[PDB]
Image (cartoon, rainbow over all chains, first blue to last red; front, side):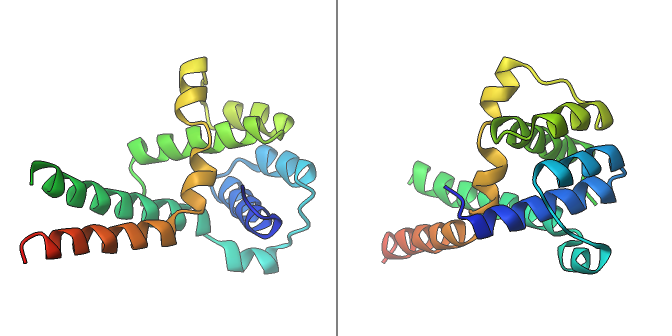
Length: 74
Length: 76
């Protein structure tokens, strides 16, 4: 489970991503469906956040993999 | 900037999140705009992934440290 706080942050991050990538119709539709009231001011806090989080986690996952592999042969 | 490979994976994860969490109108529109085709295979592979990753930073930092400690005590 995601708490409502995590979910509202995740959805704002998705919304920012959709706009930023030029999927303006998906952004419109999703803001309504997720009942997101976010303006361009609030958005500043979310700019690039989804990509950032994704990239941070993949890098950690790659580190976990390398560590596990050295432990797997060991 | 993300590679096309990584952007495609991210986009499939977003698509799966939208479908599985009930944002159906957004799912439909997003696959059209992002020029993405989903199937049952992809649906299963990307199921829960975006939500999983979103919540994973501390758990993965912890796992990195736990693993490094297993390695540290293992050559000790």
